[PDB]
Image (cartoon, rainbow, N blue to C red; front, side, top):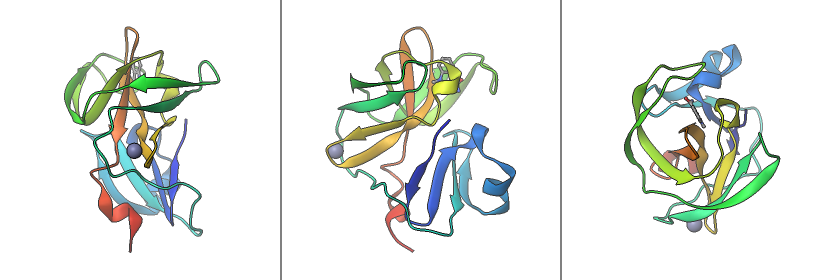
Length: 140
Ligand SMILES: Cn1nc(C(N)=O)c2ccccc21
Ligand SMILES: [Zn+2]
């Protein structure tokens, strides 16, 4: 579980989005597992714009922030989980590290701020959904 609070926008895993998220929707994408909803207050998190392939993510199923090297945002295949079956997901960066399904929402961060959130993985791999290619999050 976890969200990005960038201004009056809550960024969540689409598969973990609440009735309130859909009742106050902005943008969503099934192939990216990303949903942005509206908020009644500006947030405490800033977004990264960069091509960094290193940072740190929160792994809830360890209560640890792990340093990680991670791929650039691109197309990958995922295996069956509690939410989705074995499918492909886009704009998804991968790294070596522990992730279960419940680790989704945990933030990934580089020097430039928030890179994205846990969304995918398996077999000592963790997959992050990129929010760096969503520049509109900073404004409006
Ligand atoms: C981080 N993570 N997200 C999923 C998913 N949404 O299917 C997954 C599945 C297996 C292992 C790790 C995983
Ligand atoms: Zn950075």
